[PDB]
Image: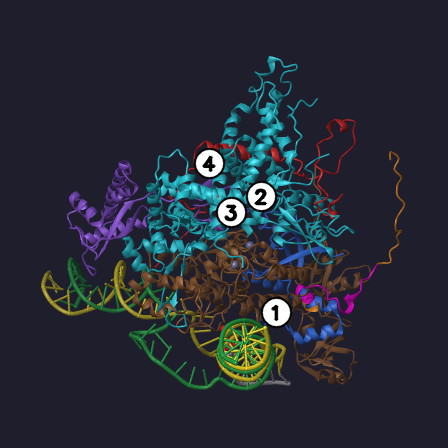
Chain colours: A purple, B blue, C brown, D orange, E cyan, F red, G green, H yellow
DNA sequence: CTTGTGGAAAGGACGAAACACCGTGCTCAATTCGGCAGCACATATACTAAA
DNA sequence: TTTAGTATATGTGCTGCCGAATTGAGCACGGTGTTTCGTCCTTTCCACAAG
RNA sequence: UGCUC
């Protein structure tokens, strides 16, 4: 699979749409699970355990969806969830479990849950100066000056 | 120029300058090395100290502090080359009095 | 009605204040942006491209094509600079040692200088004294650098600061995570263990985990210099008005005018003779374009850093074409003339164009003995006397003598060659036109380029000069021969 | 210095340029001032 | 610190004036210097220098210290000039936590710098008498009560008191009184029995003399840090954990300083009995909350003990590091998109990683991940390790590992925020200057009405105000007003990120 | 090989990412209004020292009518060193 | 002996790449001479341990 | 508690790998200039089959 | 490079 083939590669062409759809569906499923866990409000520990989703569970869910024809292994969904974690949208925890319906890792199980971001967007990004690509060439008196700036002009006009 | 076939003039080498200094003839040395060799009139801005053109300073976008100045052309070439090397010579002019 | 504005003032330069320019000041000084790597157009006229190298908006180098910025010819054009933007910053080879010194002076975490409050006050009091000379400034810099290198921990933020040195060429290495023989600190242990993923994916990282110190690329150095407090800038012995620490790392290159880069149009073949600076700037633009192309196409980091180092080396050669730490595979093939090479050397600007330069109204001839002339007199041939002219101002005393000289003309030995009127500075050649009408219309104040006649003081010198007596001012006497004759008693001084 | 004077094209301070010359013109320093009537 | 100097100059020019902002910038750039050299370098009169130094030290912006030969040197505090921008946030938080009385108290303390309790309470009463009407007068009793309540909470602190001259070296007076700080009477308010009623601006000996007060910005910084941590933990787990951590921080505020790696540990019983009764929460629920927070991979709290039932401690430095990482990833996401943020979090979690490993763990096709990596490199978001095989450091024979340094990235982002606020202030001043003609026109046409409002006020002056040519310019006036409002809002909101970054950079240093 | 560019890049290159809109709520608006009030009231404060006007053209009877009058705060000379007394 | 429709080849622009076909590969230093940076390394000062 | 031993700690002190200098000029001339390695487009000329 | 001195 490494030198050729792969569940994502189709005829030596990476399927960005496929991975995007996988990420969106997994995030929607995890968000719905977390919402159900929060609405249950039975007990904080039970809430956190219910919001958690094992790799095998989400894998079987994706298989039931059947978005694509290629068979997706458990490690594929694991990598998708790892990419989602790298997106800052979900959280994974390794719990100790000898054997069960997953039986993937020896004595360990990865549980994933949808988590909200730490803080909302900061104040720097709300100003054109923080997202400016030529911010280095800013100067008081010159061609690029805050007085005759186009970014701030369009931002205030909007 | 250098050669006779190229219609070149004589060279007042460093030793000739040393002899003229030893004699103390300041005006003769000035006329030889400045007036009769590479005399030129440049325009310098009294605000930023940079070199202008036609009585105008493109740096400050003004012409009130620009003034003419006599200078050897080799000295202006040196100043330009130094400005190219990021070594900016800022000239602070003043009245001759 | 009319505003009072002074025409000309007798301005005299007082002193030259050296300094540095920031990228913003470079943009402000420059007129256009050079982005095209080519020189001429595709058409058979081979006209210079627009917004590219050799553009006439940055001056002129041909007698036929005038400057586009100022409507003047080559003789009156002073030239204009241009600015070229670089994708990645590069270290300035000239200030590279200064960059290392500053990095050793300041902290690599908070950008503050490695000095206590007491030492800061002491240095400020020692620097505030009037009459500070260059030697004293350099000595204070040395002392402050030594006392900063003595310390190893920061008193402002508490971050550790190891040794900063030079590795390879135009690369700086900061030994932050140094090997500690005694009990190791938590910081170095955390840094060493943070390579878990790297070792898992690449085992070769584990054997080479050592010697993995911080590499201060131009980006990090510039980011650190941009956050240096202005209070510590005077402590670096750098004048704040002259420049800033962020100016040592160059992001824009100042392409000089065409007056410095003369181009010869060799119509005898399909090519033109250009200086080395033009080729260096073309190569720099090509490297910037290649780096941008690799960034857009997503190249590997290894080749990206290779191109960055190649750009740094080419910029250093453009500044100083004679370095020592040049790798063999990166060594230039031919020899180019950089600014340093044009400044230093026997044929440099200081020794070749400032200290000793060529002048006009001078001749060189063989000498022959003639004892019939006084010791203070020298014989000049008629042929040379007719070429070396002296500008005499028409006054109330020598009016008739200049009239007669003009009537004689450039053919007869006693005479002149050109007349410059007082009102208009348009010269008039005496070989053409009625010389009598010109003689009759000689107003007071005019300049007449009279031939070298008897009684004119003339310098006579022997090129190899040992003492001042090798050059003496004699009285010229015109003679029909073709050699310089003088009394032989004056042979001992000239040797 | 002398070298900088030679480079910048100005008369060096040494030699004949150490001193300055004045013109012995017929003048009257501090001439009489016209009196102000209104003030 | 050029951006910092520019921001300080802009603030001092917009707040105090021109002849004083020059002295302030000179002090910030050159540091401690005597008065004569400052006056010589500035190029102004000596009286102006004295007035500038006095009006600056009044607001606690600059300090004076003695040295050899009895010379006095004035040093400016750039940190205080930067905190000056946080006055609106201070007023808002003191109005939220307290009543309008404390709001006006803090406003007067910040606008005057140093004042006595009697003066500030008198000013508060005079200003509040305008808020209410119907002959109701404002007494000093409630104002002094609010002042002492703010004092015992460490929001307002007594200024350094000059030591007694008679007891300390009685004789020749020194050039400077050498004000010292005492922690005993730092928050002790004086007993002032005199009372009074505020005047309604009709326009028709001091017991607390020498005791000056000021706003304790450290307490405001601590409160903002606590609020930020509470909001973070609320967005992460739930509002119950937010209330729990708020109670824990409220309990820890008094028994801790403003800089410590760990706070004093608390037990479960005290946190339970101190929690508001408004929440129907039992002991086991609190224990579950604490033990699940201790297992959080962000390390907001820690056990750090088992005695007294459930013993837990709060991690402040770890929380600030998490907030800084959140800010950095959020700005990366908003500046380069979600994929670049994914790559950033990947290279952050993995301390060292290469291009192929990044592409394998991120599932981002080639020619795009390397582009974003190089873009982040060009912006100083990460540094390369460049482990060399040979001391030659040749690129063709070395490995390049990507690694994000949180400290340098945070410093760079703080500098970027400073320069952004500077540019916003410059743009606001430019918009105000270019339109000052229309501003004066509007001011005059509105003062035509403001004058003779009641006395000799004829109705024939109401239909001629809009008759002028200012009507079509009202659109430009409204545009300028909304632009200035949005610029001020952005400047205020960037102050939160500036505070986060400054706290992160401060709590990570040792100052050894 | 990289293509040659005839004209220089734009002075302000366009970006597909726009700034996040500002936070809304009573708190932000109140802070904005308070900052504006501080701007308006701190310039008229005696601490805001203005540039001393000079070079008066003439003296007139209307001077006393146009004479700018404003109360001046008295600094505490006990805490301030002696070098700042007028 | 003249001719032509189609074919091959030769010459001159032209663009990707980097002046050496392949990746190698050498020698000599041109003579001081004043910086230096490394290492090393030494000696003593200070602090811990045995009596 | 105090004298003796061990370690560090910086200083200082002797090398060895760097970077920089080496008369003034005047005069003649021969060389060669950046290119060149391979691909494609265009134009021309001549192997046979045709009058 | 050759020279001239
Ligand atoms: N015929 C002749 N040979 C020369 C000239 N200059 C140098 N050479 C020869 O070339 C060798 C030295 O070359 P250089 O004089 O250094 O050449 P260069 O000065 O670098 O070349 P340019 O910089 O183009 O003047 C000597 O061995 C000379 O024989 C010259 O003007 N004429
Ligand atoms: S161009 Fe204007 S908006 Fe953009 S960074 Fe510069 S000052 Fe800010
Ligand atoms: Zn100027
Ligand atoms: Zn020009
Ligand atoms: Zn530091």
Using the image as rendered, state which of residue E186 and residue C63 is in the foreground.
E186
Vertical position of residue B18 compared to residue C71: above or below: below
Residue E397 horizontal/vertical position (percent): 35, 69
Query: Badge 3, how many Cα within 10 Å: few under 14, some, many 20+?
Result: many
What is the CA distance from the residue labelled 1 to the residue labelled 4?
A: 56 Å
Q: Are marks 2 and 3 on the same chain?
A: yes
| Residue position for label 4 | A156
Q: Nearer the viewer, mark 2 or mark 1?
A: 2
In which quadrant of the rendered image does the C terminus of chain B lie? Answer: bottom right
User: Is residue E496 at all visible to an observer of this figure?
Assistant: no
Q: Nearer the viewer, mark 3 or mark 1?
A: 3
Determine contact: label 3, label 1, CB under 8 Å.
Answer: no
Kindly give the residue lying farthest to the top in the view shown. E459
- The part of the chain drawn in magenta is D4-22
Q: Residue at x 50, y 27 (%)?
A: E475
What is the CA distance from the residue labelled 3 to the residue labelled 4?
A: 20 Å
| Residue E276 in magenta stretch | no
| Residue D13 in magenta stretch | yes
Q: Residue at x 73, y 63 (%)?
A: C407
Residue G27 horizontal/vertical position (percent): 42, 86
User: Mark on residue E10?
Assistant: 2
Residue C332 horizontal/vertical position (percent): 43, 71
Q: Is residue C167 left or right of residue F3?
A: right
Q: Are marks 1 and 4 on the same chain?
A: no
What is the CA distance from the residue labelled 3 to the residue labelled 1?
A: 46 Å
| Residue position for label 3 | E418
| Residue position for label 1 | C350
């Amino acid at each position: 699979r490494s030198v050729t083939g792969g569940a994502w590669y189709s005829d030596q062409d990476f399927e960005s749409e496929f991975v995007e759809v996988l990420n969106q569906q997994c995030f929607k499923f995890l968000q719905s699970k977390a919402e159900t866990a929060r609405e249950s409000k039975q007990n904080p520990m039970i809430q956190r355990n219910s919001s958690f989703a094992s790799s095998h569970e989400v894998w079987k869910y994706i298989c039931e969806l059947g978005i694509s024809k290629v068979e997706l292994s458990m490690e594929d969904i694991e990598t998708i969830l790892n990419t989602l974690i790298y997106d800052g949208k979900v959280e994974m925890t390794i719990i100790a479990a000898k054997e069960g319906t997953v039986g993937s890792v020896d004595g360990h199980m990865k549980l994933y849950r949808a988590v909200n971001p730490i803080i909302p967007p900061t104040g720097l990004v709300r100003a054109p100066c923080g997202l400016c690509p030529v911010f280095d060439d800013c100067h008081e008196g010159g061609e690029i000056s805050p007085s005759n700036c186009i970014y701030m002009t369009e931002w205030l006009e909007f | 120029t250098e050669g006779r076939s190229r219609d070149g003039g004589l060279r007042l080498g460093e030793m000739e300058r040393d002899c003229l200094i030893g004699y103390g003839a300041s005006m003769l040395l000035l006329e030889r090395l400045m007036i009769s060799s590479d005399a030129f009139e440049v325009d310098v801005c009294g605000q930023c100290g940079l070199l202008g053109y036609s009585g105008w300073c493109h740096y400050c976008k003004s012409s009130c502090h620009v003034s003419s100045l006599r200078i050897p052309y080799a000295c202006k070439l040196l100043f330009q080359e130094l400005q190219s090397m990021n070594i900016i010579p800022r000239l602070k002019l003043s009245k001759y009095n | 009605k009319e505003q009072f504005r002074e025409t000309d003032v007798a301005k005299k330069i007082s002193h030259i204040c050296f300094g540095m320019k920031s990228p913003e000041e470079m943009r402000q000084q420059a007129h256009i942006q050079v982005v095209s790597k080519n020189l001429y157009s595709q058409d058979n006229q081979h006209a210079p491209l627009l917004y590219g190298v050799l553009d006439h908006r940055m001056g002129t180098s041909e007698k036929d094509r005038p400057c586009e910025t100022c409507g003047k010819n080559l003789a009156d054009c002073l030239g204009h600079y241009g600015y070229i933007d670089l994708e990645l910053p590069c270290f300035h080879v000239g200030y590279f040692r200064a960059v290392i010194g500053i990095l050793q002076m300041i902290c690599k975490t908070c950008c503050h200088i490695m000095l206590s409050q007491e030492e800061k006050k002491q240095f400020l009091d020692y620097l505030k004294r009037p009459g500070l000379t260059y030697l004293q400034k350099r000595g204070l810099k040395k002392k402050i650098s030594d006392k900063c290198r003595k310390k190893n921990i920061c008193h402002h933020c508490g971050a550790f600061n190891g040794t900063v040195k030079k590795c390879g060429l135009l690369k700086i290495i900061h030994e932050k995570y140094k090997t500690n023989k005694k009990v190791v600190d938590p910081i170095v242990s955390n840094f060493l263990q943070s390579f878990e993923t790297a070792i898992e994916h690449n085992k070769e990282v584990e054997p080479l985990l050592g010697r993995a110190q911080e590499n201060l690329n131009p980006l990090v150095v510039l980011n650190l210099f941009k956050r240096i407090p202005a209070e510590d800038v005077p402590l670096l012995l750098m004048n704040p008005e002259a420049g800033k620490p962020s100016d040592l790392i160059l992001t824009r290159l100042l392409v000089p005018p065409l007056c410095i880069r003369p181009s010869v149009v060799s119509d005898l073949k399909s090519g033109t003779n250009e200086d080395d600076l033009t080729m260096k700037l073309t190569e720099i633009i090509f490297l910037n374009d290649v780096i941008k192309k690799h960034r857009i196409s997503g190249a590997k980091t290894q080749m990206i850093m290779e191109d960055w180092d190649f750009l740094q080396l080419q910029c250093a050669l453009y500044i100083n074409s004679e370095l020592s730490g040049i790798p063999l595979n990166m060594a230039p093939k031919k020899w180019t003339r950089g600014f340093v090479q044009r400044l230093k050397g026997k044929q440099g600007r200081f020794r070749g164009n400032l200290s000793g330069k060529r002048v006009d109204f001078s001749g060189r001839t063989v000498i022959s003995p003639d004892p019939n002339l006084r010791i203070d007199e020298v014989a000049v041939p008629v042929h040379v006397a007719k070429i070396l002219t002296f500008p005499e101002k028409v006054n109330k005393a020598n009016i008739n003598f200049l009239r007669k000289l003009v009537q004689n003309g450039p053919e007869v030995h006693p005479g002149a060659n050109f007349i410059q009127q007082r009102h208009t500075q348009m010269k008039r050649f005496l070989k053409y036109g009625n010389r009598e009408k010109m003689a009759q219309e000689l107003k007071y104040g005019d300049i007449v380029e009279r031939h070298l006649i008897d009684g004119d003081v003339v310098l006579f010198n022997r090129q190899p000069s040992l003492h001042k007596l090798s050059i003496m001012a004699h009285l010229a006497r015109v003679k029909p021969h073709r050699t310089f004759r003088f009394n032989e008693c004056v042979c001992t001084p000239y040797n | 210095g002398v070298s900088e004077c030679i480079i910048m094209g100005i008369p060096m301070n040494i030699g004949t340029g150490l001193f300055k010359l004045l013109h012995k013109a017929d003048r009257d320093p501090n001439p009489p001032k016209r009196p102000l009537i209104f003030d | 610190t050029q951006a910092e100097i520019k921001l300080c100059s802009l603030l001092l020019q917009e707040h105090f004036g021109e002849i004083v902002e020059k002295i302030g910038v000179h002090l910030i750039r050159t540091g401690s210097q005597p008065l004569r050299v400052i006056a010589h370098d500035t190029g102004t009169s000596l009286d102006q220098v004295k007035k500038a130094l006095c009006v600056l030290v009044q607001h606690n912006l600059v300090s004076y210290q003695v040295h050899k030969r009895g010379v006095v040197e004035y040093e400016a505090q750039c940190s205080r000039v930067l905190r000056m921008l946080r006055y609106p946030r201070y007023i808002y938080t003191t109005k939220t936590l307290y009543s309008d009385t404390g709001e006006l108290i803090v406003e007067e303390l910040l606008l005057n710098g140093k004042l006595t309790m009697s003066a500030v309470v008198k000013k508060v009463a005079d200003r509040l008498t305008e808020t209410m009407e119907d002959g109701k007068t404002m007494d000093y009793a409630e104002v002094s009560n609010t002042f002492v309540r703010l004092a015992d909470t460490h929001f307002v602190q007594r200024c350094p008191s000059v030591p007694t001259t008679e007891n300390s070296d009685p004789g020749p007076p020194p050039p400077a009184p050498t004000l010292v700080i005492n922690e005993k009477d730092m928050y002790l308010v004086p007993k002032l029995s005199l009372i009074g009623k505020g005047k309604r601006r009709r326009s028709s000996p001091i017991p607390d003399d020498g005791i000056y007060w000021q706003a304790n910005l450290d307490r405001f910084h601590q409160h903002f840090r606590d609020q930020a941590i509470v909001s973070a933990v609320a967005n992460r787990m739930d509002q119950t954990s937010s209330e729990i951590v708020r109670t824990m921080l409220r309990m820890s505020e008094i028994t801790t300083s403003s800089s410590a790696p760990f706070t004093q540990p608390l037990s479960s019983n005290e946190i339970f009995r101190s929690l508001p009764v408004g929440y129907n929460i039992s002991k086991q629920v609190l224990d579950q909350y604490l033990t699940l927070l201790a297992d959080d991979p962000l390390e907001f709290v820690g056990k750090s003990g088992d005695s007294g039932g459930g013993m837990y401690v709060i991690n402040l430095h770890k929380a600030l590091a998490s907030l800084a990482t959140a800010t950095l990833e959020s700005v990366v996401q908003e500046r380069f998109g979600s994929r670049c943020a994914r790559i950033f979090r990947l290279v952050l979690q993995k301390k060292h990683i290469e291009q192929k490993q990044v592409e394998d763990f991120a599932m981002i096709p080639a020619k795009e991940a390397k582009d974003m990596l190089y873009k982040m490199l060009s912006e100083n978001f990460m540094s390369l390790q460049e482990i060399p095989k040979t001391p030659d450091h040749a690129p063709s024979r070395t490995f390049y590992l990507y690694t994000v340094n949180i400290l340098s990235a945070a410093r760079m982002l703080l500098h970027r925020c400073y320069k952004s606020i500077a540019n916003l202030i410059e743009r606001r001043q430019f918009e105000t200057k270019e339109n000052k003609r229309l501003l004066e026109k509007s001011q005059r046409v509105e003062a035509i009405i403001a004058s003779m409002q009641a006395t000799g006020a004829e109705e024939a002056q109401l239909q001629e105000i809009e008759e002028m040519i200012t009507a079509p310019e009202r659109q430009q006036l409204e545009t300028l007003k909304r632009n200035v409002n949005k610029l001020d809002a952005s400047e205020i909101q960037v102050d939160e990120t500036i505070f986060l970054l400054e706290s992160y950079i401060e709590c990570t240093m040792k100052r050894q | 090989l990289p293509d040659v560019v005839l004209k220089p890049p734009p002075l302000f290159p366009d970006t597909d990412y726009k700034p996040v809109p500002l936070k809304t709520g009573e708190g932000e608006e109140y802070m904005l209004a308070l900052k504006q009030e501080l701007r308006e009231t701190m310039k008229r404060m005696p601490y805001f020292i203005e540039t001393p006007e000079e070079r008066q053209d003439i003296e007139r009877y209307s001077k006393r009518y146009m004479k700018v009058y404003k109360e001046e705060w008295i600094p505490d000379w006990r805490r301030l060193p002696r070098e700042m007394m007028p």
